Length: 231
Length: 231
Image (cartoon, rainbow over all chains, first blue to last red):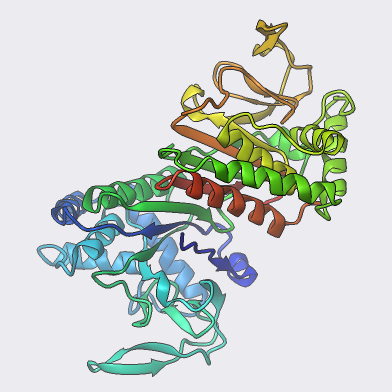
């Protein structure tokens, strides 16, 4: 099986000592029930319009505080969970892309937690969570064309041996590792801080796995709890 | 199974502040390649007859020291890893018992580390690692009949809501929670002290997981590192 062992640099652990994440590695199977994602996304959106989940405001506040700690302005560039929540509250919902994305976005919405999905095959070496020095190339998009950009010095980034794969921790994924329709080897990283109880992180992960098992029966899963707050 | 997370009481963490363990929870799949376990056990025994692994002597010495700290005599009641190593060195190999047990025994031998295997479904509530007061019943065997015994006051034990599940930390598992042939929900606890480096613990866990995935394709696995010595 394709394993993934994310490395959390000591400097990031010292910056966010309560960080704990579920790292879920998935060997995909044929996608026979795509409507699962539609049901999950509707439920997630309905559940947030009433104001929940109970830890949501506090958790997204911690992520905004953590962004400021590494130099970002979350009012402009927030964690992925806050970006999804705002779209849900403002729009009549969150638009669909494809079933796997709708599903993990649904989990992010319902459980107010950043959830990143990536293609393991595109990684060069292991994923590493580091403090950027500002000279790491990030393959992204600008004006509908490819772009070669930099993180800011001090910014927390996911990277591999080649370069940055997610900027500002969980603000924006690069193009190189994006999850497309027929990826066979997927990595999901569910990223939390202590205002989200561990049992809620567990529930979010279980809800993602059960959705995957309903959507693509036969999927195989290996997950790990990682981070300085996970022991 | 959806989230087994063992609890380590503060008093045990204070007794052994370098304790670090991999907690691996497995949803079994049909066991189609039992020869994997025999091959693993053959390899493990040959590696120890050759004198290895390099951390083994120091690691088992730490387990013996820790046993003495909680009042045990490891020369009479040793940790499970020492009991296996003694047998291998005396006899030149290890007999087969059951494929899953043979596999995790192989890991314990090759990586000189206590490895416990238990049926999660038999647990009443969550596993907890505690200091015994001496009045907790331990369902075990003596002279081939059921027995109700006590830990010593001060002894480190694993327990659940009902009683002790493993006496003297990793010396002897109870009958209630033993792993039988086709148990569906399995907990493996790989227990280490600082003379075994983290990278060796990680490799032990990876070799166990790789063995299970070869033995029972489709197995679902979740892992976590616990204890005061995990950071």
